Image (cartoon, rainbow, N blue to C red; front, side, top):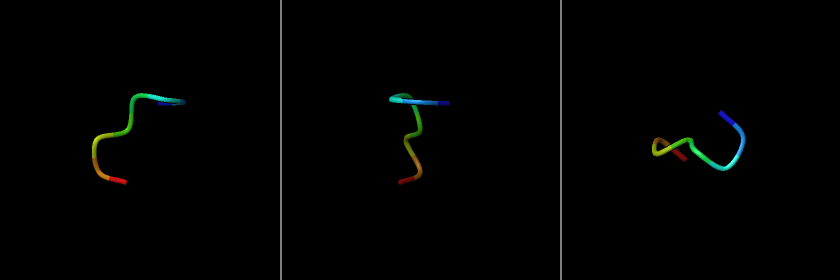
Length: 8
C-alpha cells in the first residue's frame, strides 16, 4: 500500500 510496502 502507499507508504506501507515493505517489499520496496
